Length: 165
Ligand SMILES: *CCC(=O)N1CC(NC(=O)Cn2c(C3CC3)c(C(=O)N3CCc4c(cccc4OC)C3)c3cc(Cl)cc(C)c32)C1
Ligand SMILES: Nc1nc2c(ncn2[C@@H]2O[C@H](COP(=O)(O)OP(=O)(O)O)[C@@H](O)[C@H]2O)c(=O)[nH]1
Ligand SMILES: [Ca+2]
Ligand SMILES: [Ca+2]
Image (cartoon, rainbow, N blue to C red; front, side, top):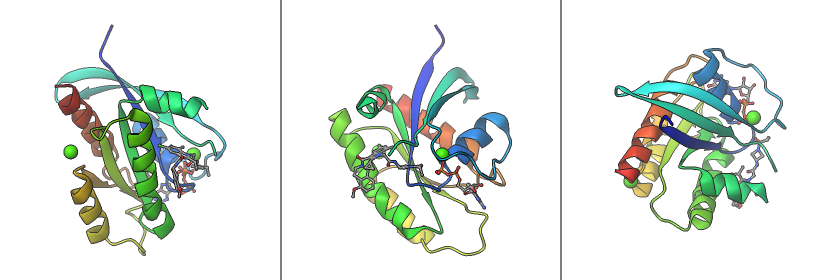
């Protein structure tokens, strides 16, 4: 009966939801993943000395969403730093989560993915400011280089712990 955390990764098509999830678990960068595959992925982690099982839903669908959202304990809000629309979508993802959870206090982390890319359309400042207003952590990640990937998920677990403690 080990501690489990139900995590849900959300965000627009092509932001790197699958790449982040697979990097975390497999330590491998998928250069392309079938965008129709929605599945749960398991990971055993130790975070600040506490061992736990992560049950991570990598969302892809475009019914049972309400249920995974309802049972989800923490949400990774992923955008890509070279996709302004994906950043604008964040607001709506957050709103839907609050709506179905019927709670203003839901563990979430804002993730700006593709930090390895030489060009970007979303400033760090913009993302930092948004996260500041939401009162949630902001992490820049690269599923390719692995920069910040562990930290993004670990930070989400720490937010879930705070919420429960
Ligand atoms: C290319 C395949 C892929 O990765 N994806 C992600 C995208 N699928 C979803 O976003 C499914 N979805 C929705 C559906 C309307 C799109 C919602 C939702 O109800 N939102 C509220 C309205 C809204 C959202 C995002 C952008 C713009 C919006 O309206 C202006 C979000 C979802 C909420 C969550 Cl928490 C998760 C998911 C998967 C989701 C195809
Ligand atoms: N350069 C770079 N490419 C990435 C990164 N993360 C994902 N990608 C690529 O962007 C595309 C979309 O990634 P994917 O995980 O399928 O996005 P999803 O639709 O959100 O699940 C794929 O070609 C990935 O290889 C990243 O951190 N850096
Ligand atoms: Ca995907
Ligand atoms: Ca907060």
